[PDB]
Image (cartoon, rainbow, N blue to C red):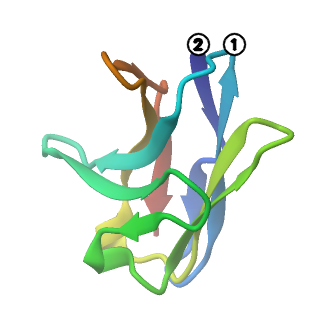
Amino acid sequence: VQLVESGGGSVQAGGSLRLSCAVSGSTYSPCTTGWYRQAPGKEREWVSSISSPGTIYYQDSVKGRFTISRDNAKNTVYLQMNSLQREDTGMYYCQIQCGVRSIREYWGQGTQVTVS
């Protein structure tokens, strides 16, 4: 299993970007997929997660602005980031936690988001 992200970049304050997390490989195990972010020199914080259908959660600072979704046929999860502000600047990572008995976790490579 491998997670590859795309969609990062520089954007003007108030603007938007859609990040993609493409899951390659295979597993028959259930997984929770999450988004995290880390500003330079700071801690990596949790942003959002999606698991079973409609089971979605968000860090409060992004509620109403970010929307996580998935396209099952493409085995991809997206993070639509609207009304971006300086506080949202950072390296964004997607991650998956899978399994029932024992868990397997995988981290994407990270994609930079810089808000004017």
Residue 64 - label:
none
Alpha-carbon neighbours of circle 1 within 10 Å: few (<14), some, or many (≥20)? few
Q: Position of residue 47 (x, y in %)?
A: 35, 59
N-terminal of the two: label 2 or label 1?
A: 2
Amino acid on which disc 1 is placed: Gly
Q: Residue furthest front?
A: 101
Labels 2 and 1 touching (C-beta < 8 A): yes
Q: Is residue 48 left or right of residue 67?
A: left
Is 33 located above or below residue 30 in the figure?
below
**5 or 100, which is in the foreground?**
100
User: Badge 2: how crowded within 10 Å, few (<14), some, or many (20+)?
Assistant: few
Coordinates of residue 57 in the picture (x, y in percent): 39, 67
Up-down relation of residue 55 to residue 34 (above or below): below
Report the Cα–Cα distance between label 2 and label 1.
4 Å
Residue 106, above or below 16: above
Which amino acid does the dot numbered 2 rest on? Val
Image-quadrant location for residue 28 = top right
Does residue 65 appear left or right of residue 40 in this picture? right
Residue 75 in the figure: left or right of residue 97: right
Q: Residue at x 58, y 24 (%)?
A: 3
Residue on which the image places disc 2: 1
The kind of secondary structure element at disc 1 is: loop
- Answer with the quarter of the image where residue 79 lies: bottom right
**Outermost residue toward the left in this view:** 42
When the figure is inspected, residue 58 is found, relative to residue 30, above or below; the finding is: below
Q: Quadrant of the N terminus?
A: top right
- The residue positioned 56% from the left and 57% from the top of the image is 10
Residue nearest the observer in this picture, 42 or 48: 48
Where does label 1 land, which residue? 25
For the point 35% across and 47% down, the residue is 36
Residue at coordinates 54% horizontally, 24% vertically from top-left?
Answer: 29
At mark 2, the secondary structure is: loop
